Length: 147
Length: 164
Ligand SMILES: Nc1ncnc2c1ncn2[C@@H]1O[C@H](COP(=O)(O)OP(=O)(O)OP(O)(O)=S)[C@@H](O)[C@H]1O
Ligand SMILES: [Mg+2]
Image (tube, rainbow over all chains, first blue to last red; front, side):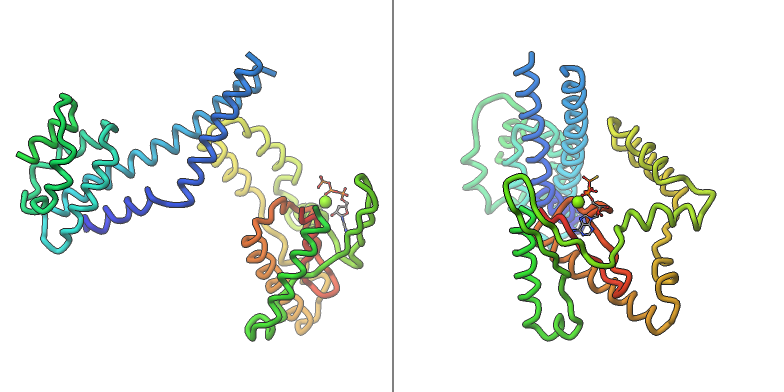
């Protein structure tokens, strides 16, 4: 069940349609902000800009929920059975891409201590290459995992 | 623009004739002729015995359902909630379409009362709609409002104009 749900959410993130939609809304925000700066008519322009901002917030919040569910369910599927063990490689890629997004790091902090470390044992070339002393949360999780 | 795109659509529909399944069903599009004279004027072929989709649908909606909203009331109600959040827009749209019922099935019961002819013409409508839907998805065709779709009330089959 957990692998099903995690693969579903992952597939929803890396969706060509959804990425095109996010790119289109981003270019719209950029162009409308450039137009508003050109002016400073202004009232309707600002109102359209604010509506674009609200649409973009909605889209980004949807993507953030998908990311939370993806990471959490990957970690729960690794801790449950041994049928799906290349979920460790996919979780690792997905987590190293989002090392700054504090959402991902909170979910990982919550669920990382229940995975047997034998799932990550063969990924020490990739883990020990990202080690640093930066006092962030990503590093406090990564160093503890390598330890 | 309209002339070039009409030519492209005609060429692709000609490609459709080379395959057994689409040729067996005569899947294709209906063409018209655009002739640009200058950069500001042209001659367009007036398709013979059609009627615009909106010009059939707006009188029929009040002829068959006299208690529903008008077309203009629905348009205005949807245009007022154009600068609002998506939740309110979808709520207004559901509220409007709960008071607006489709009437297109009558276009065939009132131009073709003979069941043999009625069945053949309704199948022509469905097939030409399917062909132009796929062909206009593949080529990104847009601006498909009611005034660019004509209903041919002799053969049943839709004609798409203004393909620019
Ligand atoms: N080539 C054509 N053959 C037959 N009917 C046509 C043709 N072109 C347009 N029409 C119809 O005749 C009318 C002419 O429409 P126009 O006023 O030229 O453009 P329009 O599409 O009505 O204006 P907008 O911008 O779409 S509101 C409309 O009701 C069309 O459905
Ligand atoms: Mg037109």
